[PDB]
Length: 146
Length: 81
Length: 101
Image (cartoon, rainbow over the protein chains, first blue to last red):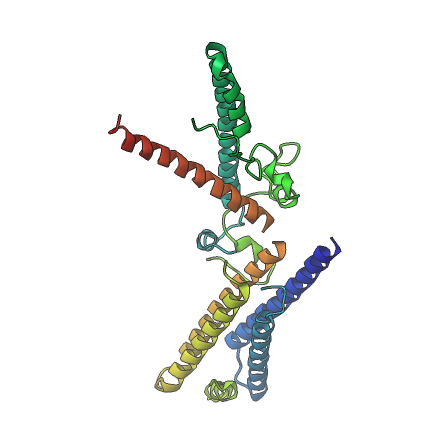
C-alpha cells in the first residue's frame, strides 16, 4: 500500500515539474513573440533576443532530455480524442455522451442477464414439471452454468 | 449424453452483475466527472475540446548537426540591418 | 499503448527539423524580401510551435490527472462489442444452419 502511494506521489511530482517547465517555456515563447513584434533594432534589444533564443533552446533541450529518461515515472491518447479536442471548447461533452453510451450498454447487459436468468429458471422448472425423469441432470445443468 | 460431471464452468470474472466501478475502487474519477451531482443538479458547464484548459495562460486564443549559435548570429545580423 | 516519452521525443525532433528548415530557407532566401515579412513568418512559426508545445502541456496535465476512468471505459467498450459480436455470430450461425434444417 505504501509503495503504490510513494509511486503515485513521485509521478505527480514529476508531472508537476514537467507542467511548470512547459508553462515557463510557453511564457518565454510569448515574451519572444512580443519582443519580435515590438523589436526596436537596438544592439541591446538584439542581445536580449539572442539570450531569449538561447534560453528557449536550452529549456527545450532540458525538457526533451528529462522527458526521455527511461527511469522516469512518465514512461493512452487515442486519435479520436485529438480530433475531438480541435473544436475550441472545454472537454466534457465527449466524455458525457460516451459515458452515457457506456451506462446504456451496462444497463442493457444487466437487463439481458436478468431476462436470461428468468428464462432458464422457468425452463428448468417446467422441464422438471413435465419431465421429472430429467430433473436430476437439469439441476446439474445449473451447477454446470452457475 | 453430453452431461459431463467432470466439466465444470466457473463464474466469469469480474461479474457484470456486481458494481464493476467499485470492484477496484474506481469511483473517484467517475464522481469527479459525473454527469450530475448527488442532488441531480449540474456541476459544471460541459463542452467539447481542450481550449478552456489554456484560458488561464496569457494570450488570445480566438481561433483553435544543428548550430544554434550560427542561426542566432544570422538572425541578429538580419535584424540589425 | 504509446509511450509519452516517445511522443515527446518525436515532437521535439519535428520542432528541431522545422526550425532548421526555416533557418535554411531564410539563409538561401534573396535579400530583396523585406525583413518585416521574414519576421512575421518567424513569429507565425514560433506561434505554431508554442501551440504544439501547449498541446503537449495539455496532454501532460491530463496524464497528471490520470487511467482509472480510461480502464473502466475500455473494459466496458470491450464487453459491449463482444456482446455485439456474439449476437452477430448467433445470427450468422442460424443463417448458415437454416440450410441444414
